[PDB]
Amino acid sequence: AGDLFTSLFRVAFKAFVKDLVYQLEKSKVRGRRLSLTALVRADIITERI
Amino acid sequence: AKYRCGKCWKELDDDQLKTLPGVRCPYCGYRIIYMVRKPTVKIVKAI
Amino acid sequence: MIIPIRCFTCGAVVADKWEPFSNRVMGGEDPEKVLTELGVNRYCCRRMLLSHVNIIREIIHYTRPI
Amino acid sequence: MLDTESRWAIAESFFKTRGLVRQHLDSFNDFLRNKLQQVIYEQGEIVTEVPGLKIKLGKIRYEKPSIRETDKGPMREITPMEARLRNLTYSSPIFLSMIPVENNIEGEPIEIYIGDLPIMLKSVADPTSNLPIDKLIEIGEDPKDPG
Ligand SMILES: [Zn+2]
Ligand SMILES: [Zn+2]
Image 1 (tube, rainbow over the protein chains, first blue to last red):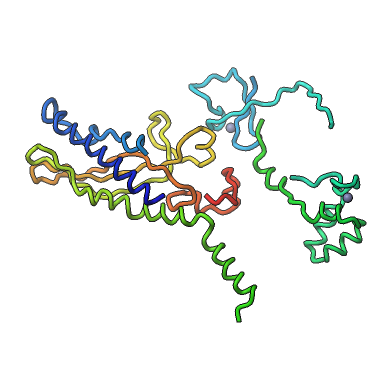
Image 2 (cartoon, chains in turn purple, red, blue, green; image 1 turned 30 degrees about the horizontal axis):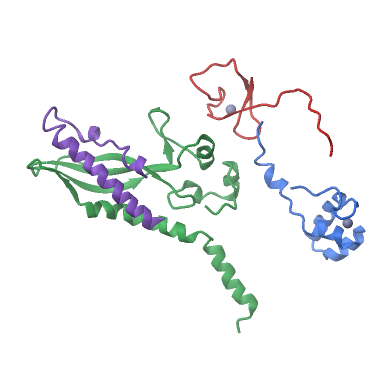
């Protein structure tokens, strides 16, 4: 279980990071000055797991 | 309908007319309730 | 769950001999001597008492509400 | 000399100290203790195409298993029986501390809720792994369940 959850969390965490840069390249460079708490969208790791 | 707030096998009984925001025990706030057995007499064959 | 009323093989009543037998065996007596004193002579009726598991004691803590 | 009873005493001690699902519990406890931090340390830090905007990741921690009642505010702790009865998932929230850096200026660290992690029963993150038999019966659990 630990070995497989390591891979699962590694895959599910880089998709969460990839979503953060997408909302920092476009959402705050053009349009507003945003905070980190708003752009996380925490329900990405949860649904994948 | 007559219900029963389930914290164990038996707790205080509540009925349907008690309207709340959702399903919950009025006395303790627990979120699981159970239907009671109606007092109709049941015939069971003893085989 | 609870002790059967009758032996499965023959129709002898065994449920009323469970409490004396179990009380005396956990008191340190020999099971064979207790069974012979109680009048349980056929091995069909002795397996009824020697293999019963009292599960209702555990189940009364998780009874369905209904 | 070791007779039958001594060797059986050794084996019985093995079974008492370590249960029958130790291969699961050891693996999951090792995961919780090391691999969560290892994954984000091997991630290192988040850098974007903006010249001077990056986030450096900190530590991770998890809470006790809890749920949020349709945004009722605070999270309330639940037991495995309630999760079974209400079709919930027995999981705990995980928080990641991040530092937003704007052109080599570190700024104030912030702790971010990043998701929910399902909890294996009888593991180190399970609050029911330490309860006595009577307290396990009180919350509606089978005392002999191995998890
Ligand atoms: Zn109640
Ligand atoms: Zn018989």
